[PDB]
Image: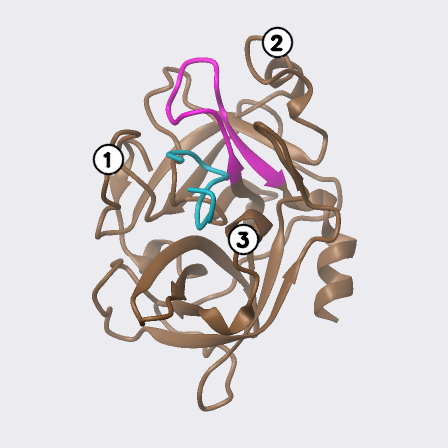
Amino acid sequence: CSARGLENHAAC
Amino acid sequence: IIGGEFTTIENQPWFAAIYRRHRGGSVTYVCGGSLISPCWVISATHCFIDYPKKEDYIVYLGRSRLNSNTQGEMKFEVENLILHKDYSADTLAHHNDIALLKIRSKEGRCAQPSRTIQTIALPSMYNDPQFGTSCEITGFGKEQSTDYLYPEQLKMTVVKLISHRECQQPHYYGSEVTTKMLCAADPQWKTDSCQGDAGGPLVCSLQGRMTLTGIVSWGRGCALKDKPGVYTRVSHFLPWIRSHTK
């Protein structure tokens, strides 16, 4: 959850 | 953006800043995007996939700072939010990581081009610069992998296009990278895109014109040795883009 791919992700 | 330099919207006037409102009413930055026509911003599907409701999003053009107004900026609601039907994501790769936002103001208008707001050209079909070509990336993403905050000021940097062959090496990403993606990196791995830069532009000079060659999509870490940034290869999605903007 500190990566490109996880922006605006609920799981994070 | 890790490393690189601070900039302003005049140096990337197609750059779109995309935010989401929350229930309660806070607004948070989501992702970058690129204005490809007055009514259309192009970005990455992974930016939205989790919260796909169009009413939740706000798009600004002409913005140089993250959480303060830039003189001349324009704010838009999202009329249409179009995610790619074939999107998929694994441990790492995001496939078909492309999205279109049709923008409209409260006054019902699309973008008015100005000193701070312009469109960026799409590439020609299946035509990309050669590996080792220098291109630029722009965004409000983290300046360091460990940062908690995003920078308040827009940044950009330069990375070099990497061959498919190199990027598919097992110590890189193996087969996670496909022909619909482009890899780019710094030879010293000292500068890169990072979290918060997704959806933003990879721009290369192509036949003496600036061209939206890629869209920031994914990578492992940021500015990490043997782990390039991975970009959606725009020149492989032109039918999808045209079909969905007609």
Give the numbered dot on residue B193: none
* Location of residue B160 in the rendering, given as x and y in whole percent from the top left corner: 48, 26
Q: What stretch is highlighted in magenta?
A: B217-232
Assess whether mark 1 and mark 3 are in contact (beta carbons under 8 angstroms).
no
Chain shaded cyan: A
- Judge from the rendering whether residue B127 lies leftward or rightward of residue B42; answer left or right: right
Report the residue at 38% width, 39% height from top. Answer: B195
Report the residue at 35% width, 37% height from top. Answer: B157
Report the residue at 43% width, 52% height from top. Answer: B31
Give the numbered dot on residue B147: 1
Query: Which residue matches tag 2?
Result: B170
- Color scheme of the displayed model: by chain
Query: Which residue matches tag 3?
Result: B50
User: Circle 3 sits in a helix, a strand or a loop, which is it?
Assistant: loop
Chain shaded brown: B
What chain does mark 2 sit on? B
